[PDB]
Length: 315
Length: 315
Ligand code: NA
Ligand code: NA
Image 1: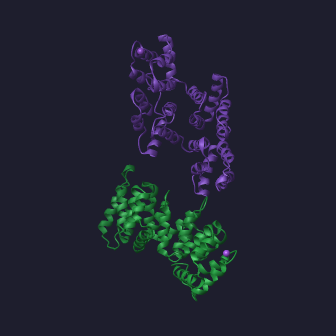
Image 2 (image 1 turned 135 degrees about the vertical axis):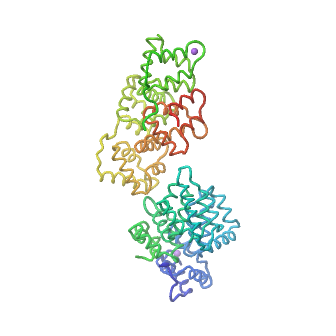
Image 3 (image 1 turned 90 degrees about the vertical axis):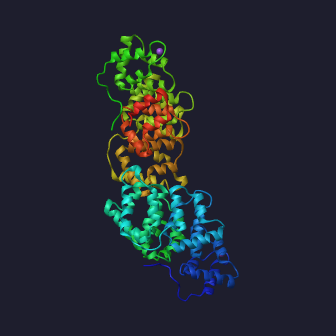
């Protein structure tokens, strides 16, 4: 378990900066050298390489990578070079700036990050952009979906693990009676239970719900709700039960079928490589009976593929 | 299931003719009597009432209804009095005579009627007007849309149900590769598959298409085509999968939002009352979470409303 990318042995930031300068200097690029260094260092080490590049090369590593590289390869490398919290912050801003909101990106990040990470994200977003994340969410999404995202962003959830069996039963009972008639869905109920109860409590509510309804909570969420609100509730449930399997499903859906959602593919591979990619891989193979490696290999190409395959770790 | 309007018990054509004559004779009209008779008889019985009116009243029932009644109420009653095939024939001619072609009416009828009905329509159109339906379609529509309508009109479709799994896969595969690039849509492909394959084959192609592309065929039709050609392909797909839901959507779109398309409202309610109105109602409520009855009641008024509500059957 854990991630694929780890801190390098023999790490020499100045030498790595020299390798990267040699790779980019003059016409042409040695992409293999860029990959061979950066995909073999963790995020913290990459920042030390940025620092060493500035002082020993007298140039800006991020500017140089941006100018040298293009398209999806450039996106993966620049994402790799970005500090963890700022990467999340940048991806949320990109999902909202304008436009036709990337609601799936909002859900993926806000449902899956831990409370201290969400706090850091809120803080950094405001510092960087001079606007609150919550305010931007309110302008760019609406209705029940909007209420879910605001709750995740504010941290409207109990962070302890107190278990009252009687309260677990009433929550499950509440969700059951709500499933009784087609007009009877109480989305406010769903929102409140799924966004406010602590993780232990919720894992127990899911077990009790199955017991009294004979249905998994996910089944009823799908039958009873729709749209981005449904997707948001499903992501909270999945991230509570098995976060690596949540990400394995995001990866699958970004590649399977007609077209490729490279922006999601890239973001998940970059953001999870150091955390739980080994787990994501195992869950992917359990769920889909194919390796994640093989999906990446069959759905991408070029240097873009080469670097994704290292973030994947292999097989 | 089936329709709302059925053959009346105790049917006495002469008495009905007397009731209708009394209702119209002299200044003023008893619209409730006209509705109470005609909306409670089926189309075949209405023709027997026309016959009885001629011989026992010595007048022409259709002329008298036309002179007495006006606007949308008159349109529903005269449509009700018209033999099934001639009603279709009249509606197609009305959609084309002149002008700025009612392309939606052409699609609705030609995509939804069964082959023997299309044959009867072609025959009756030529007899009545001295022009072929296909020729009028060619003069009044163009391009790919025109090719679709001509195919539906000629009956260019296999009417058997032979299923070759290998041919189902290649059709789906063909539609997939076509969805790969923005310039890669092969509308000829779409036309040929959707207009020529038999219904069993096609229902299997839709399932396989979803499997290999992860998209419903309707989604790709919308992203890949536009205009009346898109609408025509969507109507063929919907009529293959769930014809009552096709009509429930026509009704919805004729009433929802700004304005009312009474000509479509009337034509669908008249033409489907004896066939599948109970199914249309159920699909309407499933799709829109409101009864069809309530839409009619909230969007029409007067005697026009009264008769539509009986064609709807109620709630
Ligand atoms: Na260069
Ligand atoms: Na009169």
